[PDB]
Image (tube, coloured by chain):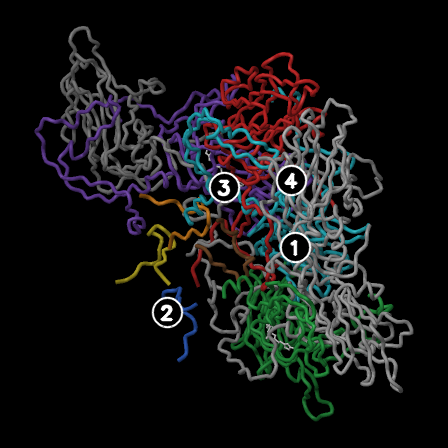
Chain colours: A blue, B purple, E red, F cyan, H green, I orange, J brown, L yellow
């Protein structure tokens, strides 16, 4: 389960990723 | 479908075309209403109309948006007692299954002879605190079809519901709701009837010989509390997946009693909504 | 045709008149399968020498008779071989054939209801939580009731018929595998019955799986000399008997 | 599990919502639905059937039937007037009508409307009335000429018997309110004598005309609301 | 997360709902299910097996067995009547019957029904009864002629012994109520002598007939409800 | 499947064909019920039937809709004490695993000899306020199979459930529910039994030698409170995924005690549902 | 959002449920898992290893080691008996055993079992015991003949030294209860002299035999529950 | 997988084949247990077996269903004070990370030398009302690894958890739960140890030199209330995704203290579960 | 979102459709 | 909506089916 | 329903599997 | 996640889009 930005804005999202 | 259904443009009405004048024989404006039929005349016929592309849906004019709306049909009440708990016919409600026990909505159906539907059903308990603390007042609603043991009093053996339906609601947790199949031995619910129980010149006659469909025996499970209360569990009802046959003239006289038509008020002259005019000449 | 012939051991039974035969739950009795099994030893299966036609003690059919029962795993606790193998082994499993004979003449009138019953937990005659005693639900060839008298000190069952001895209106009893013996058409009654029990092989001593009941419904009525006695004789045949869990030997009681 | 957020509206109850509910009575197979002649599917249908109009909306008449007939009289004068009513379909005499009774279940109405009149006169009898629709804008006309100036229909009583007058839809707002409103004023309709009521010998000289109103395919309603025309100053007993 | 709205019914409890629940005892592999002769899958099955009828539903008889037999007698008169019971399958004597006992678990019943009778008479004995089903509409018939007029079956006692009488389904409402109801009145069934009971010499002159009732493939029930026929005016101890 | 399952038309009953008259030899109406079998006669056989296409399902007549319904089988009660907390055999309940301890539903099964199922299970705690404020009364239910340390009293060491099941419910949060595998060493649950403990003329005999399956030792975790209470946690039970073998005649005599058949009332004559008639001649 | 209904069980807590939980310490990469000789994956394994049996379950002996040895004696008489224990694997002397200790963690047990005996005698010494498994049904046998009648194994003491006796699974119920239960009684096992214990000159005349019990691939348990064999009538300090 | 995993038939046991007699040389029943190995003899070997197709899974006999069960391992307690709020070492709990502080479950592991796992973790706060109203009592649990500022008292600066974990639970909202990675510098958790701190004849020796993994400093955030309380927040623990190495003999002597083996009771003779027999001859 | 008769029975479902 | 045995064990599931 | 590790970390997940 | 008009009517929906 993931990438389901339930919210529109980007500022709202999980902790980013890593690379 | 979507768009048409989301945009609510399912049942659209025709538009008003353009007309020209008519110095012609056939007179559409003339028909003989005695045929019992209804005229078919339109704007375009009578006048020199223009051209209006319409955009009004007759969606909300469907027996489902006309009927499919929740309505108070009963207000179960329990003025608890702690003095005598249990006792016969106490602290538990029971009420005969029906609609005619309360107007506005009774009105509404009665607009048709026969009706059929799955019913929604919702319970809105409201706990009035007559004490300094209401505690935790659990509740048990259930349904007693015919012929079934209807609780004589509060803790019968019938509140075990080993094979009956009992919905439970505890203060906080939301309104209990549920739904129901169309319950009738008949293909449709009889809103009316011109039948009787029998030849007994003392038999019953009405909507009713055909609707003994239940009753509801109630219960506030929690046991004895300290600080009193009074519970008022409101019963709303919605018609989902409805059909209707043979429309009738609406009601204009405030009824009295259910499963009957009777209007004849207690003394007061029979009153109706019609207003009086001084003269027909001026409106 | 009504005539019937049955051969089970070294024994055969005939009947020049009958009301079909009945197979309990429409299943024919047979031997246990390595699927439903559980035990681990090789069962001894006496064939013929065991599952043969044993006939019990006979009884009188009275105008005062009330009814009599026999409990199967138990009725043959003495019937040679089968009834030894019973006592020598822990696990026992077997199905039966019940031949109920009761003749009189075409000038007689009577009706017997015969029925077998899986787990026939009888009720005590006395109010309470005291269950019927061992020694009294373990009568033997002889069976129980008749319309008899006995100590009420004994944790004694219900001699009560109409309630089914279990307290179920007899008459719904027709749900159990059955048939009647209407002396005007019938002569016998033949029940055949497989092994019914939540376990692959039970204790032939502690547990009686099948219970058989015979109940006079319409009272015997002749116009003859009461010198004319019309017995009722029961014959039984373990079928597909299988035993296991060999050892010393229990004891008679 | 699913990280969820419970939204504002959650747990509420609306007498107007489409949601599912566990059905008590699982496994129930309802009585089949036999065939029954005449089933509705839209209020509209009922709205297109002409129901009779109380118009003789006058005093003692009112609790009786007469309250439905309009007798066409003598008239010593000429070019005299018969009656009038206003179009605002929720206004006694209109209201009570199968239509009115209804419309009063919705907040807004629209389209054309149909008024039909019938001569319960005689056969040998004759007449010619002028009916008119005076759109919203001014006052119900005091005189015929003034009213004839707008929308109307001359009606020749004859072997036919029923003249149907259409009420076009004239309005600013695609839609009108069902509730009394000075703005959404639909106007007036009135009837007058064109000629007279002539009857040859030994025929009565007054006779009646029944009047009705059914909808037009124009027609349509919206915003359901609870009715006007019925106060249950009860309760209802048992 | 998922913007969700909690619906009205939420958190409730229904003694009649299909929902899953965390199973305590995870990883448990239940005892295998061995094979067992005779397993049911439908009440119906039980309903199709004829159970005996208490009919001699009379006084002292009742707590005994006799309460099941019906002796066919003398009858000095002729064309006389035997018994009657009413069809409403939840009505002592019926009720208690495997069927009745059941039906009383549901609110509604339907279809045909089967009544079977058996002669516990003699062999050399003879008789001929007339059984009849008097549909709902009137009163249980006082006389045979009156009853013979409707549904019936003449029964010739002979080498056979069992006559089975069917009770067609006659009703207005596809369905009938299991609970006593004047409306859903199923009717009456009665039995009378066609001829007599003749017995040659030295044979008893009274004899019995047992009666039973099993269902028809017609049959079907619905709307489960808790029974009638059993009040636990206990409790139950330990 | 859906439609058939949603429309509930899985098990449908045949229709009644049309008949004509029969002046023929073979008489289907004549059979000899002594064979113990059941007649096979139908409408079409006996009368001159018509033609009715049926539409009744025997769905609700399935051992799963007959059995699969929640029923009170126990009412755990705790009249708390604050005076002595803990102490031996207090403020914590324990109860022997079974059904026969309470009718209506006991009745229902008993209709069959053997039975098998996964059981639903639900707890309906109801907190009666005997004080001026109930606080936060947490709860611990759990299950004590054989042979296991059953709490001697309230805080044993057994309430650690290091390897047992304990469900926790705190006032507000909804009814605890859960389910369970079919627990028996046997392939099916013995509703009855004609066995004993042993040859001991004092051995046990019944449904019961075969059902020592538990018990439930209870607990109100929260510690000592000020204002008293009494808790009544109702135990409902539902049978899901059920099977049944060898039907039996229903019960007509009010029982007494469980794991036994015994009816013999205390003095009162044995009473049954059968009613008395004046005469067979009139019904 | 998603019209949802919160089900009964919701919000509870079960010491026996499989559900996920936000992991505090996000982004943590645990110490690698090096290789380690001997890792278990199933209790079973432990259950198949024979652990020693306390059998000399007698008085003063008990708190010591001896509590493990069984000295094979003189025996003036012949055909005399050695010992007995009962099979119900949760019954001292059994219980405490790696198996027993365990089984007492589950409610039900099943399958065959293995008893092994070893001669801590001498080399020049000789004997022959008869061991027997007396299935459930009767009383632990008073005499050898009576016991020899069921399941047994004659054991010839010799260059080998260990005789292993199997305990077949005999039961009605596929499964047995771990808890003391008259029903689920597994039976008894006993040991007797077949011949004697003969020893040539100047060798002791009593010697010991150790006994053990490991499982069979038959074996299996279920319904986990908290143990019997350990009451923490503590607490535990710091 | 599903079926096998849903039906729980993953680890199935072999069946018992059929045998015949053997009047042959090789005697499988004879082995020398001194080899330290275990015999391999079976039913089929010793007797004349039959044929039983089995159907018992060793699923529930897996280190994960043996271990994977929640167990009380600690009962944090806070007898609040309103008199002195804050003060040193008050109204806030702290407790050393471990298991051996409480039996039944301690027992259970100890069955193995080494162990490894991700731990579930659940908190069951229970608020006992010692007042006439408990208000809104918020709570803060958190975790203090080594070496970290452990709150001296109630509001340190450490309750800011700028980089620590603090779970918050407010009366009503459900039980806090969460999980955790396997925390050890080592490849596995040492249930035991035969090591010391050092050569110091006063060094530490046990499970413990290797497990200073934390502690938990607690806090009831809400501030000063009027009516008192006492909070008891129970700490349950579950082992998910477990592995185990080198099994050990279970414990039979009631311990005392943790991180030690010590049994030697205070005076009382060392007691064990073994029962005494009169005679070996009769069981 | 639709046609997800979360419940088995048909009696339980949204307001029907239109056609 | 269906066959979503949200729980592992089989004992936990809806009322069975019919056939 | 399964394998929906609603949470990122692995330490958070159901009871493992069996093999 | 989007375009899941959980509700029937259009009047009920998120803030429109942009174009
Ligand atoms: C006229 C007319 C209209 C109707 C419709 C009848 C619909 C039945 C009422 O439905 C309910 C049922 Cl069956 C049970 C309950 C109930 N509430 C708590 C327990 O049972 C509530 C309602 Cl609205 O009947 N006659
Ligand atoms: C006859 C007959 C019928 C049954 C069925 C027995 C089913 C077991 C009861 O199931 C429960 C269990 Cl195992 C535990 C709990 C429980 N509640 C709180 C803790 O444990 C409740 C129930 Cl209904 O047994 N004999
Ligand atoms: C022996 C032995 C066994 C273990 C296992 C140790 C597992 C660590 C305990 O896990 C917890 C942690 Cl790290 C924090 C919290 C916590 N609760 C509130 C704040 O932190 C609770 C637990 Cl059970 O250690 N020695």
Image spot of residue C73 (x, y percent) = 72, 48
Of the two numbered discs 1 and 4 in the rendering, the one whose residue sits closer to the viewer = 4
**Discs 1 and 4 lie in a common subunit:** yes
- The answer as to whether callout 3 falls within 8 Å of ligand 1 is no
Number of the label disc, if any, that sits on residue F58: 3
Real-space CA distance between mark 3 and mark 4, rounded to the nearest whole angstrom: 33 Å
* Residue indicated by mark 1: C199
Instruction: Name which residue lies at 72% across and 81% down.
Output: H32
- The answer as to whether callout 2 falls within 8 Å of ligand 3 is no
- Mark 4, Cα crowd under 10 Å, few <14 / some 14-19 / many 20+, is many
Of the two numbered discs 3 and 2 in the rendering, the one whose residue sits closer to the viewer = 3
Of the two numbered discs 2 and 1 in the rendering, the one whose residue sits closer to the viewer = 1
Between F137 and I7, the one lying in front of the other is I7
Real-space CA distance between mark 1 and mark 4, rounded to the nearest whole angstrom: 26 Å
Of the two numbered discs 2 and 4 in the rendering, the one whose residue sits closer to the viewer = 4
Task: Reply above or below: E154 against H205.
Answer: above
- The answer as to whether callout 4 falls within 8 Å of ligand 2 is no
């Amino acid at each position: 389960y993931f990438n389901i930005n339930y919210f529109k804005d980007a500022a709202s999202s999980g902790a980013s990723r890593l690379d | 479908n979507y768009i048409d259904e989301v945009l609510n443009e399912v049942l659209v009405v025709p538009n008003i075309k353009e007309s020209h004048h008519t110095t012609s024989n056939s007179a559409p404006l003339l028909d003989a209403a005695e045929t019992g039929h209804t005229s078919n005349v339109q704007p375009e016929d009578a006048i020199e109309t223009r051209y209006v592309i319409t955009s009004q849906t007759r969606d909300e004019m469907s027996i489902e948006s006309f009927l499919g709306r929740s309505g108070c049909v009963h207000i179960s009440r329990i003025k608890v007692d702690y003095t005598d708990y249990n006792g016969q016919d106490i602290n538990f409600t029971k009420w005969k299954i029906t609609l005619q026990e309360m107007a506005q909505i009774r009105r509404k159906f009665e607009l048709f002879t026969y009706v059929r539907f799955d019913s929604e059903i919702t319970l809105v308990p409201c706990i009035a605190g007559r004490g300094d603390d209401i505690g935790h007042i659990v509740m048990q609603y259930m349904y007693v079809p015919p012929g079934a043991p209807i609780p004589s009093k509060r803790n019968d053996f019938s509140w075990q519901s080993g094979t009956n339906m009992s919905i439970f609601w505890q203060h906080g947790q939301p309104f209990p709701r549920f739904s129901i199949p169309f319950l009738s031995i008949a293909s449709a619910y009889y809103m009316f009837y011109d039948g009787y129980d029998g030849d007994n010149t003392s038999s019953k006659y009405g909507s009713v010989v055909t609707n003994d469909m239940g009753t509801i025996c109630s219960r506030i499970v929690t046991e004895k509390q300290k600080l009193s209360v009074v519970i008022t569990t409101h019963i709303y009802h919605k018609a989902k997946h409805t059909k209707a046959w043979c429309p009738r003239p609406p009601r204009a006289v405030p009824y009295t009693h259910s499963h009957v038509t009777n209007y004849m008020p207690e003394t007061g002259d029979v009153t109706t909504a019609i207003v009086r005019r001084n003269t027909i000449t001026t409106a | 045709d009504r005539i019937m012939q049955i051969t089970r051991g070294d024994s055969t039974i005939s009947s020049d008149d009958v009301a079909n035969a009945v197979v309990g739950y429409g299943v024919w009795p047979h031997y246990l399968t390595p699927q439903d099994a559980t035990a681990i030893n090789k069962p001894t299966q006496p064939d013929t020498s065991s599952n043969r036609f044993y006939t019990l003690e006979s009884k009188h059919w009275n105008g005062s008779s009330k009814g009599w029962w026999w409990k199967l795993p138990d009725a043959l606790k003495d019937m040679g071989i089968f009834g030894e193998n019973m006592y020598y082994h822990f696990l026992g499993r077997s199905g039966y054939t019940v031949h109920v004979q009761c003749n009189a003449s075409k000038f007689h009138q009577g009706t017997l209801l015969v029925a077998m019953i899986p787990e026939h937990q009888l009720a005590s005659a006395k109010h309470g939580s005291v269950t019927a005693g061992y020694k009294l639900t373990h009568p033997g060839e002889a069976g129980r009731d008749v319309s008899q008298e006995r100590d009420a000190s004994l944790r004694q069952p219900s001699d009560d018929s109409w309630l089914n001895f279990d307290g179920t209106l007899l008459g719904n009893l027709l749900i159990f595998p059955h048939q009647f013996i209407n002396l005007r058409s019938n002569n016998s009654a033949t029940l055949i019955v497989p092994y019914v029990n939540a376990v692959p092989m039970d204790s032939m001593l502690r547990h009686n799986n099948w219970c058989l009941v015979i109940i006079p419904i319409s009272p015997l009525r002749s116009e003859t000399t009461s010198s004319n006695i019309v017995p009722i004789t029961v014959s039984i045949s373990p079928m597909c008997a299988e035993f296991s869990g060999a050892r010393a030997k229990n004891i008679k009681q | 599990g699913l990280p969820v957020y419970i939204t504002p509206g959650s747990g509420q109850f609306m007498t107007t919502d489409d949601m599912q509910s566990p059905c008590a009575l699982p496994w129930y197979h309802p009585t089949k639905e036999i065939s029954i002649p005449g089933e509705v599917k839209n209020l509209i249908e009922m709205c297109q059937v002409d129901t009779l109009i109380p118009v003789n909306n006058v005093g003692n008449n009112v609790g009786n039937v007469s309250m439905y007939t309009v007798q066409l009289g003598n008239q010593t004068g000429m070019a005299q007037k018969v009656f009038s009513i206003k179009v605002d379909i929720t206004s006694t005499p209109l209201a009570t009508t199968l239509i009115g009774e209804i419309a009063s279940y919705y907040t807004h109405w629209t389209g054309s409307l149909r008024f039909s009149f019938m001569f319960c006169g005689t056969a040998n009898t004759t007449l010619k009335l002028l009916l008119a629709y005076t759109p919203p804008g001014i006052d119900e006309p005091t005189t015929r000429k003034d009213a004839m100036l707008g929308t109307h229909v001359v009606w020749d009583v004859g072997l036919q018997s029923t003249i149907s007058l259409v009420v076009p839809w004239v309005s600013a707002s695609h839609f009108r309110l069902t509730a009394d409103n000075k703005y959404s004023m639909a106007g007036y309709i009135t009837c007058w004598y064109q000629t007279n009521l002539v009857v040859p010998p030994s025929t009565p000289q007054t006779a009646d005309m029944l009047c009705f109103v059914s909808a037009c395919k124009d027609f349509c309603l919206r915003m359901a609301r609870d009715t006007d025309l019925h106060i249950q100053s009860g309760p209802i007993e048992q």
